[PDB]
Amino acid sequence: STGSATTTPIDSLDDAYITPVQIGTPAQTLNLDFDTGSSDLWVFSSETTASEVDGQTIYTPSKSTTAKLLSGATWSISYGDGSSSSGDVYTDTVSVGGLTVTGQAVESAKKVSSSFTEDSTIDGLLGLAFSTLNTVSPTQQKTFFDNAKASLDSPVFTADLGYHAPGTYNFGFIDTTAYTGSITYTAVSTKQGFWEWTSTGYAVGSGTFKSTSIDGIADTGTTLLYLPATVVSAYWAQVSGAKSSSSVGGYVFPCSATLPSFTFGVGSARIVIPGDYIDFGPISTGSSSCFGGIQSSAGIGINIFGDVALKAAFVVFNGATTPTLGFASK
């Protein structure tokens, strides 16, 4: 089997991407944030504290003839951005782009933090990291991908995120028309539960490539590119007037600037992030100070190849017995 679904930016900055997901019988379609940096499929629901729901579409398990309470199961998650959610668990039928899993754990939110409530466009998350990170207790649950894997034509999914445009998540096949050149594959460590890999280096603009190992995670659920302070300083030094602002919480730059590209290494291959992808617009409405899309990972504890980086590539998440990651230009 295979699946193919379009993923759409939630706003003009590509702050996140939502993908429609069918849950239950009859189908209830919710727009979920596909997150290769976590492993829970959780939704706004009829059980979510009413004051914490503001415009989201909710899953109502009592209206699904295939929903079953997973007795005794609870979940609770905190994300790197400080947001959180928790609740109980149902199993139900879940379909993405024509690919159907029966008995998928659907984690129903009883509580969500303010940042979720405040984002009316995201109805929940669909985790695509390794199932070892799933938070369901006392019986850990499998991700949608893990459940689908054996049925897929090939045990892979691909992320093709657009810049200020829709893109595609495919399951079970590699669309050879979706990228240019060849796909370069690189080793993955699953020791922390993430799609963790090592970039071979970087360049700023038309500058020379610096060969250096950068361990990080491929994370579709993180907006920006978070890299070591040395790398980030080298990037922003090429932008007149750019500075790290402790008050704003990262590098800012004059909105009048033209940003250089940023290249990262995948083996001997190179992925080029155009400068425009690194512009996240005014820090507040009407400001001439703009927020940068490359930020320091210092104090995160891990480097994160988030959407800024991934949307410059066609990315293969290869869930073979020994997983790997593939990157192609597009």
Image: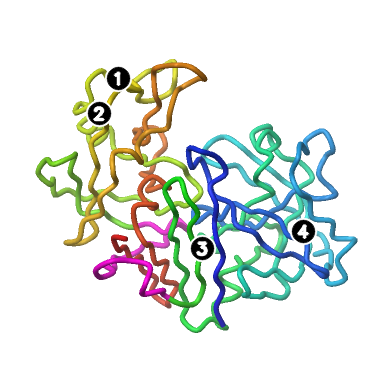
**What residue did someone put label 3 on?**
130
Q: Is residue 290 left or right of residue 33?
A: left
Is mark 1 in CB contact (under 8 Å) with mark 2?
Answer: yes
Quadrant in which the C terminus is drawn: bottom left
Crowding at dot 4, Cα within 10 Å, few <14 / some 14-19 / many 20+, comes out as many
- The correct choice, above or below, for 205 with respect to 38 in the image is above
Tell me which numbered mark, 4 or 3, is placed earlier along the sequence. 4
Mark seen at residue 236 = 2
What is the x, y in percent for residue 220? 47, 52
Crowding at dot 2, Cα within 10 Å, few <14 / some 14-19 / many 20+, comes out as many
- Magenta stretch holds residue 279: no
- The correct choice, above or below, for 322 with respect to 45 in the image is below
Q: CA distance from mark 4 to mark 2?
A: 45 Å
**What residue did someone put label 4 on?**
89
From the image, state whether disc 4 or disc 2 is nearer to you.
2
- The correct choice, above or below, for 220 with respect to 256 in the image is below
Tell me which numbered mark, 4 or 2, is placed earlier along the sequence. 4
Residue type, numbered disc 2: Trp
Q: Residue at x 44, y 15 (%)?
A: 247
Question: Magenta stretch?
Answer: 174-196
Q: Nearer the viewer, residue 247 or 315?
A: 315
Q: CA distance from mark 2 to mark 3?
A: 34 Å
